[PDB]
Length: 635
Ligand SMILES: Nc1ncnc2c1ncn2[C@@H]1O[C@H](COP(=O)(O)O)[C@@H](O)[C@H]1O
Image (cartoon, rainbow, N blue to C red; front, side):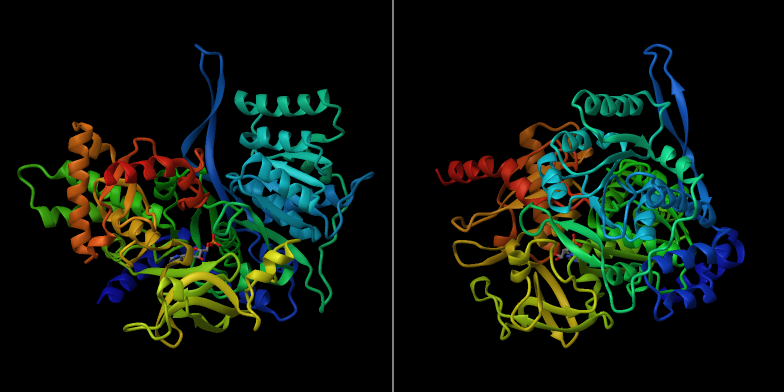
């Protein structure tokens, strides 16, 4: 059977693979972690002691290369990873915490805010745990946020320390020049031998000097060396009836201004011991590649859930996924969380390889099997026990495809920053943490409890993992809870039967075409991902119009040897074939579109940090062009 075959691979792994064998969670440690009165920092401490000698975290090895022509010295990555142990990481954490707690003039205290501007890394983990160690509130800033937004965040949270990576010092210094509250700027992920990083650092210190700031600019290495000669810091443990704030996770609802979702000491502890499948509540060996930012809930769960199981968390070299598959192939994780964008990258690799190897003497469906086998064992590392997709919808055909590549199920996990990570797993309500739910009719979008095969409406939730609200935004907080205490997800679902729900789309993505047919734009975007010719797609509509438009980023091979006209016909053809396969309505098919050779990225503000389309920014970028296309066509 399919499970039988997969279970045969795992038995081989545990017989043969000694890294895997050595990373099995310890029952005694898991027991201690799930102990009743344990608070967040005690959990961290227990894990670190319990797994002290094991590799905890890894990063790419690197070299420093001097170009004798330019004279410039740059950090260069090597194709391997280096690890540090639980003991070493915790030692580093304790050093930062001692430095902060025992500072002679201006020490940090429980409840102070600390702001962090980074990706995900050993240094990030060090700073984040040190906050936890002292009961400081972590504010992990989104790299994708505009400086104006960052300043808004800092104004609101009044942190006493700001920490930043070199690539982010430009935004960090503008925040500090603006008269915000941090007293120290701590640079991390910092290699002074790299000229570009050194220049960013020395610029940062000299601009703050020139401007007469009293901010102390320093390196994380220097903070650690200082704490190394200071007494041990106390471990923060709130009293039994207290649940102080521990973490703010900023998230942008249906339009991009950040609101800080409040995670209390208790809610943050669920990332170590809550029951998702990627949370630390299991005995699965956790060797994983962390490629999502610590500013997002999925990044934090990926780190803390792995640490909770005594596994090893490897950090991706880059935040834009440009090293993602090289990293996965080197790490060979025993688990992944996919976002759909990553499934896209796998599909594009497949299409490319298949097209390339499809020579005259080929047997094609045996070739398909061979390309997928190569993807599986080599591109993705061949050590997977489990796979999950989440954060955004995956179309049925791409799910079918990915399962064919992985040769195991691809679990669909639905959750949110506000509601919690688990909520729905493969269409099944997860209890715990869900306490109850209901569907509420949405008459103006055509979703009623009395709809056709299955009831439809907005999902409203109660769960143990729901946030209490957003930090200092109580009128915004008021709107996400109904009179009875239900969290309004803003998501449309269908109820197949009790506790079994199918995600449709966000309420705000449901559009009524003029003839009165509703379309779901994010869902249709997912469907057209299966076009072998489409690299990215943004689908756009107007309720004043009868049909959809799109902005399509073609693949490199789709582009090759074609002019604009030919490229459009080829895309249009592919679009029709995909629509047929997914049994789409005629009105669900983009009837024209813009060709865009510039990919949507984090850097140009069109992708989020977890590679989701940022709809408000895409509407602002292409909306005028698109409406003009509507007008030209109507003419
Ligand atoms: N498995 C999934 N399928 C479809 N959409 C999802 C899934 N998981 C999360 N989402 C979407 O992501 C939103 C939460 O985003 P975030 O707070 O960034 O995790 C949800 O309200 C959904 O719109």
